[PDB]
Each structure stands twice: as structure tokens, then as C-alpha cells.
Image 1 (cartoon, each protein chain N blue to C red):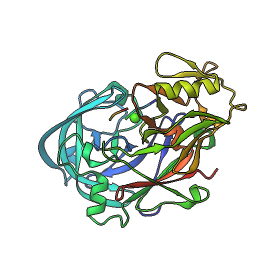
Image 2 (cartoon, rainbow over the protein chains, first blue to last red):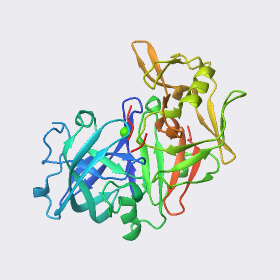
Image 3 (cartoon, rainbow over the protein chains, first blue to last red):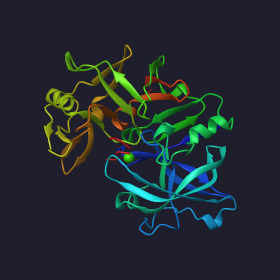
Image 4 (cartoon, chains in turn blue, yellow):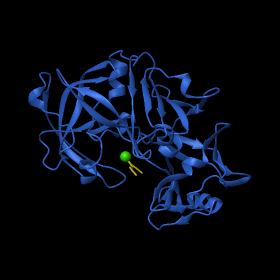
Length: 325
Length: 7
Ligand SMILES: [Ca+2]
């Protein structure tokens, strides 16, 4: 793959996407979840006492470039999962880019959900204002200051399991074979340390199901999570039924559904009918959109697997275009 | 489904 190019693996039915990262000297390959909703780089380690037997664990003793650090860290994610441990320093190879002396967080403890998932840890791609330890420079910050990328961007392509899965992240460039037409520039609000954007409105057919709302571009979230009122309005448009747990039951047959279209900075971006169905379990389908009690939306994989995004940490801004498919 | 700080 080209320089700074990282092929991704689509886990299950577009649940999450992970890529291989080499850490240490000579180095081991770790499968990390690429997460724009957080900014800590943490990995399962041999110090871990409740980690998955299947996870690849970083071993400080096997890296001649490991450097001890006296600080500890602890993280708690929106979904209730967590991890904690100690800081360390080592080299990280991201698609051929060798970041020297990156702060890595070695897990000592992790939630069972991590122990049983497919990744060895997370690579945070949010802003450095939300690192859990003050003063930690994120991988993007180091790519930029070490001159490893010449443009402060990363292009993201998330595939659909229905079409073969896959995905691809490119650090410092983007791939026009993955999208169609012109990219639309959208300003980002990073005041909360996230990739925040404003959606002008949402329509289903001729119905305006929502007026402007703010949301965050989160590659680390599976669904399109909307504020209660907006989710309810969307659900009414598709005849979806509330499961009372933040999710909806929708018809498994999407052949009749119209796409959920978002108007962003004057252009149309959609959630195609097939994406309206997240998962099918014993003939019952879970919708691709859910609800949460926040005033902002979490624009997750349901949306990102339909739209290519160039993330520019420099401005900050994003460039979006419908996926080529 | 996964949901990585605030969400
Ligand atoms: Ca997640």
C-alpha cells in the first residue's frame, strides 16, 4: 500500500473497523480501532490482568525502544466501556510512517467488552484537547510535527459488509477512486475536542424530519445516534418501533424505503436504504439509527460507510462526498 | 454496536 495507507478490516455487519499498527522495536502488529471520537492510543499489554486471551499484548520487555513513564491513565467511554493502566513511550508505525516517541497507554485493566472484541486497543483521532492525560501529543499531532505528513489530513473510506467490507485510511492524502463528484468543504467546530459539524436539515422523501442540528463525526460509533425528538421523527417516517433501549425495530425489507438525506453546507449526503438496517437477528431487524439523551447527534458508521471524509486537523474542516459504489 | 468519549 502507498505511504501512510492503512487497509481496514470491517468487523461483522459494519460494527467497527480496525487496521494494523506496528509498535516497538523490532515491533509487533496490533489491530486498533480507528476512532475519531477519542484521543488516547491504548493497547492491551502483558501488565493486563483481565485482558482477552485472543488479544495481541504489547510486552515492554520485547521492545528495545520502550521508555517507562510514571503516570497512570483511566478512560471511560460514552457506551460504559473502560480501560486503565500506565503511560509509556515507544515508536509507532502507521502505514509506513514511523512516529518516534509516541506516548502509548498500556492497559492493566479493560472492560469485558474489549476483552471479547476483535481489537488490541484504540487509536484516537479526535483533538488533543480531550486526551485523558494533559500534555499528551496525539499521533496526528506527531505526524505533523515530525514532518511525516505534509498536509494535516487523513482520508477515510469505510466499506460495507454487503459489498465485501474493507475500508482504508490514508494519512496525509486522500483517494478520489473512493468517491464520486466534487468534495464539499464543511467547517468543523472543535470546541469540545470532537469533529463537530452542523447538519442543515434531514428529509425522507418530501418530509422534513429535522431542522438544523449539531453532530460529531465518529468512526468509533456504529449507528447514527440522534437526539430523542429527531430520532422519533425519523422513526415515524419509516414505521420503526422503539425497543426502549436506544434502538428501533424496523422492517427487514428496505426495498420500499426512501433514503435519509442530510443537507450539509448546501449538498446532499445520504444513508442509503440498505444502511437503514443495521442487523438482522432471527428475522427481526435493528435499525441503523438510534437515540440517546444528548442535544447533539453522533454521526457514526451508518453514515460514514456511505460518505467519504477527508479530515483536516489543521483548519479544522472536513471534505465530504458520497461513496463511489 | 460500539460507542467510543461522549456519546
Ligand atoms: Ca466504539
